[PDB]
Length: 35
Length: 35
Image (tube, rainbow over all chains, first blue to last red; front, side, top):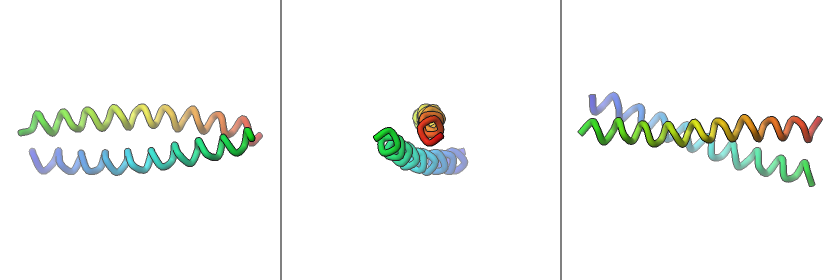
């Protein structure tokens, strides 16, 4: 059980980090577009 | 033990859902501006 949940945690952390970078890019793009 | 892991999965997944919502909104704004 420990092992199975640990993998899920690592999967989620990576997905979270990818999303933070995507959001940062999209906020920059929109700022530039509106400008 | 597991409670700590299941809790962490819950906490990370919540953050992920909110970023997914933000990405969807930002993508909408970008599409509007670029079109």
